[PDB]
Image (cartoon, coloured by chain):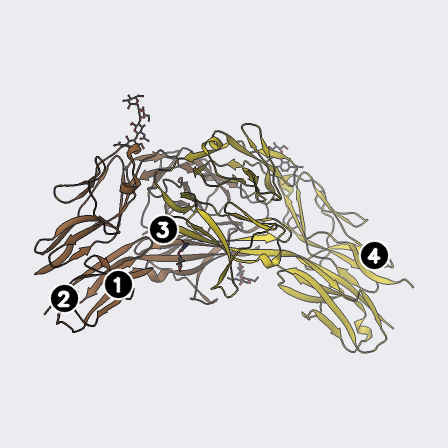
Chain colours: A brown, B yellow
């Protein structure tokens, strides 16, 4: 009577510690009631692995907590999927990427910053790369016991500002800021446990002798970063000079040398030399230029920004009934950036068609069933289902 | 007879850097008949006199900056761009731009970082130098807890466990657990004061045994970077990425069409060490966009690097001297080298003639035209000049 439709579809990424474990739930409607079958991305069904992987009584895929020595890649590092099958047909859920992580101790270091008097600075929380995925800055702390907290930047005024990217920004540092030592608290997403940095960083304020031209922390005149739509993005410009330089941001026109001055508003803001883009959208993508001038001279560093958007898929029509021999057409309406590939499936099998529109010119008894459109990134996947009825 | 305009025998270098304690002396010498007078000037053409205890003109033509206390630093003296003026009755010539930079010595400490590495792949160890001494301080040698000294190599032979790169960082092939049993210290040497200093912090290699497999991961999320290099110098393009199983890496160089790319040809000159590309004895033609591609069974990643190779500026005028009979044609051809070239300009007895073309032609030689001529090639960071004389018959 009716094909399967996912009511609750597992997320693309499931990350958990070996201590917590995880349980993945998948549910779908239909008439008759579809059966839920957990599978790998390649389509094979998954069974119980003692102490490691279990199919629950309610149809949930479970990974109970386990010893680090019991780690298996075939289970814990595997990409899974949910299969909802019916007499009418079957559908496959978007890729479920399971990563079980054995929790391993780490140390964060707060770096010192050597500053020319009057220039603004940004303090970094150094996080070892192996925990870099699961660890972020909780807050900043100083020797006198003052707390600086992360905020979506509604108000950029004030001396100390914690950037959305986790660094601690400080306006116009004088000698009076040199008596403080700064420390950063890190938070682990999986364990929820907090840890202070092993090393306290502190500002070294050097009084300017003579004049100095703009000088960046690095000699690299170009870089890039990735960002999410609807998330607050930070473009850093790190330069020190005396007399204190002024910074302006420009945006190049696509495939052109020409560029426009970035317009600053209640969403796009500039804190000293740093640029913050709140509530980012895909169109913010492009090539940006930071220009730093002072009386003695000037420099320019470049940045390439790419703003990602979540993948979504919709098939028009959701349902259609065609007669034997007549054409049947499916149009996949998808969104999100970037898009690497489009692909189609029928009742859980690759149809070998990469175009957003799928058309069966002469329909047979075989073609009846559920159809799916799959859009994917390296990072992501999305799925939409549609049903085809005969007569 | 034997009468000739000025020509520089010794032209002071483009960059003069010295510590407040050491001091400096800049000497400019030029020939001529009669003996030319040497006069020190600024870039604007104004003459400079003696500033007591700070700047002094020696009558033999030396510009002297005796040692001074940090309190005595003057922007108008120590940070100034100078030039040498050699004048005679026939004309005058101005030397290349001389950038004088005096530096008050600041105490510093370099950090030898501990680096986390997955077993089996290569690692490069950073020596952090405070950005304010970054100009004047470089890595002299590496030293380890066992007392083994590693010295910077020209990269003649890149085989072997340990290779100190031209840039000063320490590269290590196929790190095993045993390579983490020891701790490393880098020794930095200050260029101006000649003093050597230990890192005072010993970095240690942490070898983490792989739990499952992981795709290529770079130290930073940046997919692009650029760097500058000088001709004849050994240039290092770093690719620092970890994966398990240990990944294989490929270097490419984009075509000027920018769509196409070619595999980098490895030879006795251009050679890569386990993912780190070294270009020895660099030339201008090595410039371009490079791509480091790290692919593995689990996945792949590619980082881009834009390299620019600079060559020193030099200028020479084809005739050094010529004598015209008032026959109307007269010609000077400026031979210049180096990269990049921002501007070419001709000067007459120390003043711009408003001609930027490499070949200066004076049609209609007249008594107004007698004097010294100069070709001037400039980039932002350097300058060069050539001298020539014009005589009448
Ligand atoms: C998930 O994996 C992690 C490892 O990746 C695992 O955490 C580790 O558990 C072991 C226990 O099996 C811990 O060992 C302890 O270490 C502390 C020091 O940190 C010791 O003080 C403890 O004392 C023990 O020693 C006695 C004998 O010497 C025992 O008889 C006594 O009962 C105590 O157990 C003990 O040695 C280890 O520290 C942690 N490591 C980390 C980083 O947390 C975790 O248990 C795994 N989770 C599950 C659910 O299996
Ligand atoms: C600020 O400094 C910049 C240099 O970073 C100056 O602009 C550059 O000038 C050079 C020529 O020397 C050009 O090749 C660049 O294309 C210019 N870049 C830009 C972004 O303009 C600029 O003139 C300086 N501005 C002031 C007011 O001094
Ligand atoms: C050059 O400047 C440095 C300061 O940067 C001077 O070194 C100082 O010397 C005094 C003694 O006269 C010491 O008490 C300080 O600790 C030193 N400071 C540093 C940073 O070394 C040095 O004397 C100056 N040189 C001359 C010739 O005066
Ligand atoms: C090596 O890695 C690259 C990605 O770093 C793989 O994919 C290439 O990705 C680009 C997109 O940036 C596509 O345009 C190319 O077509 C992809 N390459 C191919 C061959 O399709 C690449 O596939 C990897 N190569 C191998 C042999 O694994």
**Foreground: B315 or B371?**
B315
Q: Quadrant of ligand 2?
A: bottom right
State which quadrant residue B143 falls in. top right
Report the disc number at residue A334: 1
In which quadrant will I find the N terminus of chain A?
bottom left
Circle 3: is it few (<14), some (14-19), or many (20+) Cα within 10 Å?
some
Separation of marks 4 and 1 at Cα, in angstroms: 79 Å
**Mark found first going from the N terminus, 3 or 2:** 3
Q: Callout 2: helix, strand or loop?
A: loop
The picture places residue B186, in percent across and down from the top left corner, at: 56, 35
Circles 4 and 1 in contact, beta carbons < 8 Å: no
Circles 2 and 1 in contact, beta carbons < 8 Å: no
User: Which residue is tagged 3?
Assistant: A156
Report the disc number at residue B301: none
User: Which residue is tagged 4?
Assistant: B31
Report the disc number at residue A365: 2
Circles 3 and 1 in contact, beta carbons < 8 Å: no
**Foreground: B335 or A101?**
A101
The picture places residue A278, in percent across and down from the top left corner, at: 33, 55
Chain for disc number 4? B
């Amino acid at each position: 009577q009716k094909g399967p439709v996912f009511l609750k579809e597992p997320t693309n990424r499931i990350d958990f510690s070996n201590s917590t474990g995880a349980e993945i739930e998948c549910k779908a409607s239909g008439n008759p009631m579809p059966e839920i079958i957990w599978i790998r991305s390649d389509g094979t069904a998954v069974g119980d692995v003692p102490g490691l992987r279990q199919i629950s009584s309610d149809g949930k895929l479970v990974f109970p907590p386990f010893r680090a020595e019991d780690y298996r890649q075939e289970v814990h590092a595997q990409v899974y999927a949910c299969l909802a099958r019916n007499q009418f047909g079957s559908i496959i859920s978007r890729d479920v990427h399971v990563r079980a992580v054995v929790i391993q101790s780490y140390e964060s270091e707060a770096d010192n910053e050597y500053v020319i008097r009057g220039n603004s600075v940004v303090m970094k929380c150094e996080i070892p790369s192996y925990v870099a995925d699961f660890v972020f800055v909780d807050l900043w702390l100083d020797s006198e016991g003052r707390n600086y907290y992360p905020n979506n930047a509604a108000e950029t005024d004030g001396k100390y500002l914690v950037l959305p990217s986790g660094e601690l920004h400080i306006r116009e540092v004088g000698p009076e800021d040199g008596y403080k030592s700064y420390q950063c608290r890190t938070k682990h997403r999986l364990t929820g446990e907090t840890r202070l940095s092993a090393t306290k960083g502190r500002l070294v304020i050097t009084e300017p002798v003579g004049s100095k031209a703009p000088t960046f922390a690095t000699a690299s005149k170009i870089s890039s970063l990735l960002g999410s739509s609807s998330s607050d993005i930070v473009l850093l410009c790190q330069a020190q000079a005396f007399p204190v330089p002024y910074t302006r941001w420009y945006k190049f026109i696509e495939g052109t040398t020409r560029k426009q001055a970035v317009v600053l508003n209640d969403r796009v803001k500039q804190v000293s030399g740093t640029l913050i883009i709140k509530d980012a959208v895909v169109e913010d993508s492009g090539k940006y230029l930071c220009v730093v001038n002072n009386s003695v001279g000037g420099e320019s560093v470049e940045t390439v920004l790419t703003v990602t958007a979540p993948l979504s898929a919709k098939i028009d029509p959701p349902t259609q009934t065609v007669d034997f021999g007549r054409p049947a057409v499916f149009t996949c309406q998808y969104t999100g950036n970037p898009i690497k590939t489009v692909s189609w499936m029928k009742d859980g099998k690759a149809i070998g068609h990469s175009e957003p529109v799928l058309r069966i010119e002469s329909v047979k008894k075989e073609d009846k069933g559920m159809y799916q459109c799959f859009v994917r990134n390296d990072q992501e996947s999305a799925e939409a289902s549609a049903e085809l009825k005969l007569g």
